[PDB]
Amino acid sequence: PSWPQILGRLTDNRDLARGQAAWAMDQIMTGNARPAQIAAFAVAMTMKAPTADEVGELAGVMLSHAHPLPADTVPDDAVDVVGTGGDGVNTVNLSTMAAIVVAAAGVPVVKHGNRASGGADTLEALGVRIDLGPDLVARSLAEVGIGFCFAPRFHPSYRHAAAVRREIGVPTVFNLLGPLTNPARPRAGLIGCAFADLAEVMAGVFAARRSSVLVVHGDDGLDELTTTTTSTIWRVAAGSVDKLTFDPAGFGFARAQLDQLAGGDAQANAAAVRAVLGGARGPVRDAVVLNAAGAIVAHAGLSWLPAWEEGLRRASAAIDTGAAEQLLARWVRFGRQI
Ligand SMILES: O=P(O)(O)OC[C@H]1O[C@H](OP(=O)(O)OP(=O)(O)O)[C@H](O)[C@@H]1O
Ligand SMILES: Cc1cc(C)c(N)c(C(=O)O)c1
Ligand SMILES: [Mg+2]
Ligand SMILES: [Mg+2]
């Protein structure tokens, strides 16, 4: 295998041969790939139109190189709530807030995340330790019900890819990898995809791993279940993908305006988390509850309408009883206690 060969095949608009994407990603992750080669590969893959097999190869290499969590520390039914980002709309950290609420409802959550105010920035501002290694994330999950895997901490060898991603700016296939590379390897997730054309490829990757996952794209372009309009959902169950249209109004949700979901810096976004967890009613709470419920449905799938009703009931109660607010406080506390 070589760069001229792989790049030539991609510029010929041809799907890669089995193992070629893995070879490329492994060259990238081991510091053996020049910045020019990384960029060429990222772009060529993107323009060819990556397949699930290919994206699955890239993600597997990343996971091979990632720091794992200690054996037997991650529950068999752990769930992630994470999006590709890059939806061009600046929202409150819907996934992060949903994760807190899901953990509070009793579903173990191991959230993969990163800076932008991104999930990681907002958590840091809330006083949550984002920087914890495998052992301590495992303890966090055991003692709090939620662990946060900070992408840079667990994927240090991604450094060269990350630099190139910054330099070129343009979204590429690499933008799909975060939600597919949680180092704790949870089997369930609510997975946001900004890129409508690539949501199905993401779903295909999760299906190949037999995850129970909802890949979601708001029909307003949010990488979350949206409240402003309907959402497209790629439902992954039993190793196959269903595409459907999801309408929140179907559960009594009032239509919001995207401006009402808008975020700010880490301090603003942190305030918005505190507000939701303190019971503030309105658009942000509604979107958080909806996404929390979707994550619970994905968790349920590890065994539709009944699932959503129970998910919504459970998410609402976790906030209303103060369990969500208390969980965050316990999370802050856990991290201050080293
Ligand atoms: O949108 P960008 O800033 O360009 O970067 C992509 C973001 O995707 C993640 O959202 P995640 O679902 O993990 O958290 P959230 O929905 O709570 O923000 C995380 O915040 C990354 O920064
Ligand atoms: C996954 C990951 C890993 C490393 C080492 C990074 N620096 C970044 C980043 O800057 O976004 C992301
Ligand atoms: Mg998100
Ligand atoms: Mg988002």
Image (spheres, rainbow, N blue to C red):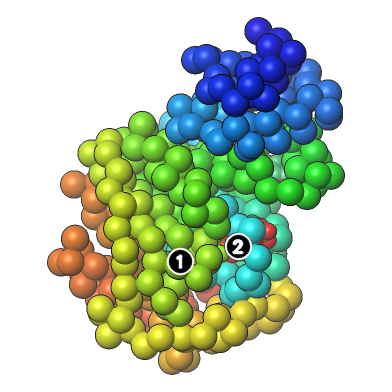
Q: CA distance from mark 1 to mark 2?
A: 10 Å
The quarter of the picture showing ligand 4:
bottom right
- Quadrant holding the C terminus: bottom right
Q: Is mark 1 within 8 Å of ligand 4?
A: no
Q: On the rendered structure, is 222 left or right of 190? A: right
Whole-percent x, y for residue 54 in the image: 52, 27
- Looking at the image, which residue sits at the far top? 1
Residue appearing at x 39%, y 38% in the figure = 204
Residue appearing at x 67%, y 25% in the figure = 11
Q: Which residue is mark 1?
A: 218
- Quadrant holding the N terminus: top right
In the depicted structure, whether residue 59 falls above or below residue 298: above
- Looking at the image, which residue sits at the far front? 12
Q: Amino acid at mark 2?
A: Asp
- When asked about the image quadrant of residue 163, the answer is top right
Whole-percent x, y for residue 316 in the image: 32, 79
Q: Amino acid at mark 1?
A: Gly
Q: How many marks?
A: 2
Q: On the rendered structure, is 235 left or right of 278? A: left
Label 2 element class: loop
Label 1 element class: strand
In the depicted structure, whether residue 141 falls above or below residue 231: above
Q: Which residue is mark 2?
A: 87
- When asked about the image quadrant of residue 116, the answer is bottom right
Is tag 1's residue or tag 2's residue first in the polypeptide sequence? 2
Residue 115 shows in this picture: yes
Q: Is mark 2 within 8 Å of ligand 4?
A: yes
- Looking at the image, which residue sits at the far bottom? 281
Within-10-Å neighbours for mark 2: few <14, some 14–19, many 20+: some
Pointers 1 and 2 in contact (C-beta within 8 Å) = yes
Residue 82 shows in this picture: no
Residue appearing at x 42%, y 58% in the figure = 216
